[PDB]
Amino acid sequence: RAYRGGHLTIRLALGGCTNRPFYRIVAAHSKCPRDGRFVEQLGSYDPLPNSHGEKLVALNFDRIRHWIGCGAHLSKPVEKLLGLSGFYPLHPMMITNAERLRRKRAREVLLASQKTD
Amino acid sequence: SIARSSVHAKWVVGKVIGTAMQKTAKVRVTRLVLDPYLLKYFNKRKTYFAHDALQQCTVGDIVLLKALPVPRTKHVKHELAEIIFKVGQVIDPVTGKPCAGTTYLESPISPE
Amino acid sequence: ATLNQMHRLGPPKHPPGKMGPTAGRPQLKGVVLRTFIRKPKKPNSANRKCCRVRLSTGREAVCFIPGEGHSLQEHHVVLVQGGRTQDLPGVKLTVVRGKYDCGHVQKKK
Amino acid sequence: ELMAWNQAENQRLHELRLARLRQEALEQERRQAEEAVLQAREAQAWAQLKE
Amino acid sequence: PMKGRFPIRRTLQYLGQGDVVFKDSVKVMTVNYNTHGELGEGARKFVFFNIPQIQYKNPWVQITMFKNMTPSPFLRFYLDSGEQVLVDVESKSNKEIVEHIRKILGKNEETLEKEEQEKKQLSHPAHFGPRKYCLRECMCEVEGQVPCPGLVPLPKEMTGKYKAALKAT
Amino acid sequence: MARKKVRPRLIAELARRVRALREQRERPRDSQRYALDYETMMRPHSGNRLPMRAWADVRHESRLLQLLNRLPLFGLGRLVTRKSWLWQHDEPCYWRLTRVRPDYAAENLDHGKAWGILTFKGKTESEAREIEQVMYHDWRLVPKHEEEAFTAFTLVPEDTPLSVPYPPLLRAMILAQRQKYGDTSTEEPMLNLERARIDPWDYPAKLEAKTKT
RNA sequence: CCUAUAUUCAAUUACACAACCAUGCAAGAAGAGACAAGUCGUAACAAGGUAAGCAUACUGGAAAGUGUGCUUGGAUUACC
RNA sequence: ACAGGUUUGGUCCUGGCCUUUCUAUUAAUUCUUAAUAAAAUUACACAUGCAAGUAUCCGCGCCCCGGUGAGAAUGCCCUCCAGAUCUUAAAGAUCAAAAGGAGCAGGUAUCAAGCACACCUAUAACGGUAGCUCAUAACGCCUUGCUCAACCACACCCCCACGGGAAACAGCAGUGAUAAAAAUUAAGCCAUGAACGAAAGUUUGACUAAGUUAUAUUAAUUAGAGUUGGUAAAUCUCGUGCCAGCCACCGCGGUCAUACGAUUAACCCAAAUUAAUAGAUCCACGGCGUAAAGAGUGUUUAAGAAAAAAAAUCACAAU
Ligand SMILES: [Mg+2]
Ligand SMILES: [Mg+2]
Ligand SMILES: [Mg+2]
Ligand SMILES: [Mg+2]
Ligand SMILES: [Mg+2]
Ligand SMILES: [Mg+2]
Ligand SMILES: [Mg+2]
Ligand SMILES: [Mg+2]
Ligand SMILES: [Mg+2]
Ligand SMILES: [Mg+2]
Ligand SMILES: [Mg+2]
Ligand SMILES: [Mg+2]
Ligand SMILES: [Mg+2]
Ligand SMILES: [Mg+2]
Ligand SMILES: [Mg+2]
Ligand SMILES: [Mg+2]
Ligand SMILES: [Mg+2]
Ligand SMILES: [Mg+2]
Ligand SMILES: [Mg+2]
Ligand SMILES: [Mg+2]
Ligand SMILES: [Mg+2]
Ligand SMILES: [Mg+2]
Ligand SMILES: [Mg+2]
Ligand SMILES: [Mg+2]
Ligand SMILES: [Mg+2]
Ligand SMILES: [Mg+2]
Ligand SMILES: [Mg+2]
Ligand SMILES: [Mg+2]
Ligand SMILES: [Mg+2]
Ligand SMILES: [Mg+2]
Ligand SMILES: [Mg+2]
Ligand SMILES: [Mg+2]
Ligand SMILES: [Mg+2]
Ligand SMILES: [Mg+2]
Ligand SMILES: [Mg+2]
Ligand SMILES: [Mg+2]
Ligand SMILES: [Mg+2]
Ligand SMILES: [Mg+2]
Ligand SMILES: [Mg+2]
Ligand SMILES: [Mg+2]
Ligand SMILES: [Mg+2]
Ligand SMILES: [Mg+2]
Ligand SMILES: [Mg+2]
Ligand SMILES: [Mg+2]
Ligand SMILES: [Zn+2]
C-alpha cells in the first residue's frame, strides 16, 4: 500500500513455529509489517543448530549487492550476519561484545578461584 | 524521443458508425473475445472517437485508427490515419483495381 | 440451445439458499407465550404438545416440544432449533430439551 | 529481408493470377458466342410469331 | 463438447497446440475472404481452424474478418511502425497460409525458448513461503533440520517455558 | 480512481486552504517557541522536557543571540565558537557571521535566525549558509585580540591509509572471478577509501533546501 | 529596502426543501391455502346418462347453463 | 457420483425431494494428560491501567505497526506515472497519488430509456454545429469487502470535516448492553521488526515466551455417545394399545410393535458423540407431437450463416 515515506531495507522476517524460529532474509519497504509484504526474498537464516551442529545461512549475494547497490539499509543482525560471512567487515559491536564476554569470563574465573579458597 | 499514449489501443481498425459530430468520426472496433465456458470466440464491439481533419468519412467505411499522443478531449483518444475501405467504392489492394463486391469493375488483364 | 444463446445467457448459476425459520442461525432464544395442543395431519393421529414463542428476532412462531411430558408455563425462556415436525403442518421449530427452562425428560419414577 | 521476400511472393502470385484470368476471359468470349447464337434464334422465332 | 461442426476446435488442448506467435510489431491482423469460389477455399478453412489457435496465443492482437469485399482472399498485418504487410492467399492451402505467416512474422523457436527460460528462472528453488510460490514453507521440513514442534514436540530444555521457569528459580 | 458516478468532494479543498491559512497566520514567533522554564526544564509551547545530558549547559551557558544582542553592529564579521567544539575539538571550530536577523517580539531580544561561513577542524567552507542550533546554549564569542589566536591553525596531513583489504570472502570472490577470465595477476585487490570520507557527527548540517539537479 | 524583511485578508448571498422513498402501526377490505364422519346439490371421469373442451358473451345458490365460431385431448363398431 | 430411497394395483418414461462424503460454528450429552494450531456475536455504549518516543536543547518520529469490514459493486488484471523517501554530483532505486483501458468482474429488464449525459473553433474567450450513452444492458434498485506473499476501504456521527452534533478502546487487556455465540483487567524487550541516537543504548500490549478453551490436528495415561423397520452396519423380553410418543425420506403406533418407552444383546464411531445451522458439491453442450417448452401470421433492423451442386413462373375456392 501507499505510504508517506520510508526506505528500502534488508531485514529478517520471522517465519516460524512456537519455540522453533526461522528467518527469511528479505528486501522490504521499511514501513510495512515484519512478516508481511516484501520486494524480494534474499536469503534464509536458521537459528537452531541442526543434526551436524550447524546454523544454515543462505545469501543471494548478486541480488544482495544489487540492492545495497540501490541504497538499501541493512538491519543490525543482517549486518552481523554479512560480517560473520566475510562479505562485510566484522560489525564493531560483534567485536565489542566479544571483549565484554572475555572480561566476564575473566572475572568469573577469578571469582571461582576466590570462592574455592 | 518521447511521443506516447498510455492507451493499449495504439493501432486499431473499425467500421464508421456515424459522422454526426464536427471533424469527429464515431467508430466501432470489433475484437474476438474467448468465452471461457464454451471456449469459443465471439465479437465484442467497442466505440472510439477519432479525429477526422478533412471530414473524409462516410458511414460504413472501414478505417484505421492511430492513438493520439495527447488526448483532444476525454472521449477522443484517436486520430483517423487511413481509409482502408471506402464504402461502396473499393480498390482491391492486391490487384489495384476498382471492384463492386466479388466482381471486378475494371479488368486487371486489360491494361490498354 | 445453440452456442450463441448459451453465450448470451452465460453458464447456469446455482441460486443461493432461501433462508428458513431460524434465519440462518443454528438456534434461537425465545419466551413462551402459550402452551397448547395440535392435531396432526390426516393419515395418522395423536395430539402433539406445542407452544407459541416469541424469538430474539421479534418474530412470533409456533414451536414443538419433543419427548413425553413437559413442564412449561408462560414466561419460561427456551432455546429452539431448526428441525421440522412432519405430522404438524406449519410447525418448523423445535424446543431444545435440557436448556434454560426446559429440562431433560425425567425417567419414570 | 522477410518483407522483401513476401513482396516477391505476392508479385509471383499476381502473375499466376493474370495468366488464369486471361484464360477465363477467353472461355467467357466463347460463352458469349454461344449465347449470341441462341438469343438470335429465339429473337427470330418471336419476330415471326408477332408478324 | 457436443454441439458444433468440428467440436474438437473448442477444446483447450486444440487452442493451445496451434503454434504461431507474432512479433511485438504486429498489432492488427485483417483477414479478407470469400464465401464462394473454389480458389478462396483454403482461406475459409484458415478462418475456420487456425484463426482461433492464432488469437489464443496472441491475446493482445486485434483480429478482424471481412467477407465478400474484394474478389480475392488476402491478409493484412498492421505493425507498430505503420508498416503494412499484405499477404495474398489464393489457391494456398490452410497449412501453407499458416506456415507462410509463421515464416514472415513469427518468433524463432530460439526466441520462444529463451523467453520461457527467463520465465522459469523467476521461481527460485531455494526460497521459502506459500505453497503457491515456493517448494517449501518452514525449514522444519528440510531433512537434517529441527522438526515442526506440531509434529515432533521439542525436548523440555528448548522450551521457553522451561528456560523462564529456570531463570525464575 | 475513476468510476463514472464519482462524487465531487468540496470540503476536502476547503479544509486544505483553511488549514494552510490558519497555519501561516498563527505561525508562532520563535521567541515564545524556544522559550524555556529553567526550574522544570520544560518548554511552555511544545510541553517538551529537555534531555538530561543537556541540563548543565542550559544553566551555565548562553545562546547565540544572547551574546549577539550586546554587539555593536549586532555582530557582523565577528567570530563565534561552540562549547562542545571547544571541549571535543582542539583544532579551531568557528562561525563567521554574514547576516543576523533577530526576533523583535522578544522583550530581551534573545532569539533570531543567523547566517554565515563556517570553519570546522580548521577547514574552511567557501560559501554562506544558515547557522544551525542557534537556540542551543553552547554558544561563546571570541574577543577581537584573541581572534588572530583562534584563527591560527597548524595544518597537518592525514595519515589514514588510502586503501584497505577486501573482506575475506569478498576478496576470495574477486580472486576466483578474475582467475576465471584468464587474468593471472596475483596483485592484491584493494579497497579505495578516498570517497569514503565522512564528517564527524558534530559537523553542522545545512538547513537550506536542496536544489534538484 | 547601509545584512534584509515585515504585514494584511478570503466570508457570504439567492432559493428550494419530506416531496420522494424506505421501515413499523392501522380503522378496515379482498384473496388464496388448510380445513368435519357438517349442509346443498351432482359438474367431470363410461356417448357419466345433454360427448367433452377452447376463445368470448350473457345468465344462474353452487357446481354450472346457453349462444357464436373453433378443437378431438369423442364415438359412428368400418364388403354396413 | 460407481450411486441409492420415494410417485403406481402394477410396468416404463419424465421429474422433483431426500440419503450416503467433507468442513466450520453453536447447542446437548460425555471428558484423563500433554504438544501444536487457532481463537470469531456485535462500525452499540465504554469505569480503570497500559499501547510513542528518542535525543546535549533544534529536530526526527508519533493509524508505521496494530484494529476492523462499516462503506462501496465496489473492483481484478494491465497502461502511465506526479510526488514523497533513500542513496549518491548526477543517475539509480523503494512506495507509488492523480489520470487512464486490450480483457475480466454479484443479483435484478416487473429498472428501458438517461436528460445535456457531446464535439468543433480556436484562442483559451467569444462563438459555432446538435449531439452523447443504451437490449453486446445505459440509467436505476438490492446484496456485498476481496480474485489473498497480498489488496481495497474506514478511523465516533454529518460520503468530506472548515464548521456542527458532540466528548469517541473498530490498539492490549477489561466492562455494560446485545447475541445461539464468553481467551489474561497477565511477564518481558532476551530474540526479530520499527522509532530516535555518532555511539554505547533507550522505548515498543508490534512481537517473543507464557495464561485460558476439546475448536482442530497429533501422541499416549484416557470411555463415553449415537444407532439396530428400509435406504443403511446391528435386537431380545416386557410395558403401551391411532394413547403416549417416533421419523432425514419412505413411514411406525387400533392388543403378538425388531420403528414408541424400558430391558437384554448387537453395531459403529471414540475423548469425543449426536442434533441444529451454514457452507463445499450439485441444473442444460439437456430438451421442446403426447410429459416444462416451436412463441396466431408475415417482412425488415441489429446480428449471424453463406461452408460443394442448381433454381425465380402458369387448369382450380387469395385479396
Ligand atoms: Mg506461531
Ligand atoms: Mg397411522
Ligand atoms: Mg426432526
Ligand atoms: Mg445444561
Ligand atoms: Mg522532541
Ligand atoms: Mg356437462
Ligand atoms: Mg347413452
Ligand atoms: Mg354428471
Ligand atoms: Mg355430460
Ligand atoms: Mg341429467
Ligand atoms: Mg365424455
Ligand atoms: Mg367457456
Ligand atoms: Mg340459460
Ligand atoms: Mg333457451
Ligand atoms: Mg373399430
Ligand atoms: Mg430418482
Ligand atoms: Mg403418476
Ligand atoms: Mg403404493
Ligand atoms: Mg461452546
Ligand atoms: Mg467461540
Ligand atoms: Mg488491515
Ligand atoms: Mg449501495
Ligand atoms: Mg516519479
Ligand atoms: Mg498509479
Ligand atoms: Mg457491507
Ligand atoms: Mg466515515
Ligand atoms: Mg466505537
Ligand atoms: Mg468520518
Ligand atoms: Mg479491546
Ligand atoms: Mg485509537
Ligand atoms: Mg458482558
Ligand atoms: Mg463463561
Ligand atoms: Mg527488542
Ligand atoms: Mg534492542
Ligand atoms: Mg509490556
Ligand atoms: Mg473433538
Ligand atoms: Mg428414538
Ligand atoms: Mg408388546
Ligand atoms: Mg430406524
Ligand atoms: Mg425403541
Ligand atoms: Mg432436466
Ligand atoms: Mg405441452
Ligand atoms: Mg405454429
Ligand atoms: Mg396464445
Ligand atoms: Zn514449522
Image: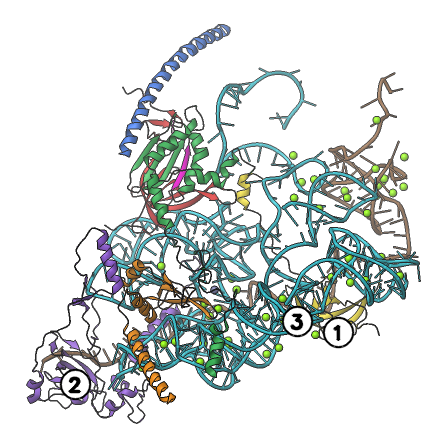
Chain colours: A orange, B red, C yellow, D blue, E green, F purple, G brown, H cyan
Q: Nearer the viewer, residue B74 or A65?
A: A65
- Answer left or right for A11 relative to H25: left
Q: Is residue E155 magenta?
A: no
Q: Which residues are magenta?
A: E60-71
Mark 2 belongs to which amino acid? Leu
Q: Are marks 1 and 3 in contact (CB under 8 Å)?
A: no
On the question of residue A74 being in view, the answer is: no
Q: Which residue is mark 1?
A: C103
Nearer to us of marks 2 and 3 is 2
- Answer left or right for B61 relative to F175: right
Nearer to us of marks 1 and 2 is 2
| Image location of residue H119, percent across then percent down | 34, 49
Residue drawn at x 39%, y 33% is E98
Q: Is residue E64 magenta?
A: yes
- Answer left or right for F39 relative to E95: left
Label 2 SS: helix
Q: Which residue is mark 3?
A: C56
Label 3 SS: loop
Nearer to us of marks 1 and 3 is 1
Tell me, yes or no, whether dots 1 and 3 are on the same chain. yes
* Looking at the image, residue H221 lies above or below residue H295: below
Classify the position of the N terminus of chain A by image quarter.
bottom left
| Image location of residue H160, percent across then percent down | 42, 70
Q: Nearer the viewer, residue F49 or F92?
A: F92
Q: Which residue is mark 2?
A: F86
Outermost residue, bottom direction?
F39
Alpha-carbon span between mark 2 and mark 3: 80 Å
On the question of residue A85 being in view, the answer is: yes
* Looking at the image, residue E134 lies above or below residue A7: above
The answer to which quarter of the image holds residue E61 is top left
